[PDB]
Image (cartoon, helix red, strand yellow):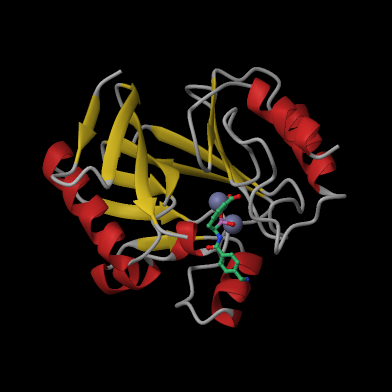
Amino acid sequence: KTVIKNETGTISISQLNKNVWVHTELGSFAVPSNGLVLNTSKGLVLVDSSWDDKLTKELIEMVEKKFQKRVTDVIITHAHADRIGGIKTLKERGIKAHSTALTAELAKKNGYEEPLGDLQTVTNLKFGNMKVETFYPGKGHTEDNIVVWLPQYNILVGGCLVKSTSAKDLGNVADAYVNEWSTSIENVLKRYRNINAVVPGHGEVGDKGLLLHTLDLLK
Ligand SMILES: NCc1ccc(C(=O)N[C@H]2Cc3cccc(C(=O)O)c3O[B-]2(O)O)cc1
Ligand SMILES: [Zn+2]
Ligand SMILES: [Zn+2]
């Protein structure tokens, strides 16, 4: 798979297909974090920003240069820093920051600028030719965590709800609901029965197996 790094190695993008890339940044907490870059005919769309504004700026600038179009939209998958840390950069550049109402409320509570709160339990978006579904499966990693589905590729962005193979514990559970997290995972497995790739919030891209791994970690 084609991989491209910033001048520092702190930012990397890896191609999943012609129009879909994973973006990965190193923040301190040293912790890598994943999101998605969608190359569409109407502009770039990101799933999740990054740890802070410095990295988010760098990310945007890298993909805008490479793909020769603007970042127009970002989907924020919950209100923690690795997801929403760059929200100030998005707002001041006129980049639309989509989220559930709950994610927006929690962002505000925690002193972040507010994303749009436009996403429902199920929301279907289209950016040029690129179809994007957002789904709130229930509480897990956080009370507000959502997943993102690309039905044209059967690619699932699990976010921090979904642990990577390298993860040997549930990680940061300060704001988690460990009794509901299994049901929420099961809700994802029920909705998306045929998955080609699953992108975890941290770690290597996997498949449906990452969902099953997460269930085992919850026992
Ligand atoms: N409510 C206090 C609080 C604020 C922010 C964070 C936070 O930014 N957590 C992120 C960074 C991180 C650091 C280490 C592991 C994970 C993980 O996904 O498990 C991980 O993902 B989080 O979204 O929880 C946690 C608690
Ligand atoms: Zn989190
Ligand atoms: Zn996380």
| Position above or below: 177 against 128 | below
Report the residue at 61% width, 20% height from top. Answer: 195
Q: Quadrant of the C terminus?
A: top right
Q: Which of 13/128 is in front?
A: 13
149 to the left or right of 211: left
| Position above or below: 147 against 195 | below
Report the residue at 63% width, 49% height from top. Answer: 146
154 to the left or right of 39: right
| Position above or below: 204 against 25 | above
Number of numbered discs overlaid on the protein picture: 0
Which of the 4 image quadrants contains residue 44?
Answer: top left
Residue 94, x across and y down, in percent: 28, 68
86 to the left or right of 82: left
Which of the 4 image quadrants contains residue 49?
Answer: bottom left
Residue 108, x across and y down, in percent: 55, 79
| Position above or below: 111 against 218 | below
Report the residue at 25% width, 21% height from top. Answer: 2
Report the residue at 48% width, 29% height from top. Answer: 204
Residue 83, x across and y down, in percent: 48, 57
Q: Which of 29/195 is in front?
A: 29
Which of the 4 image quadrants contains residue 1?
Answer: top left
139 to the left or right of 2: right
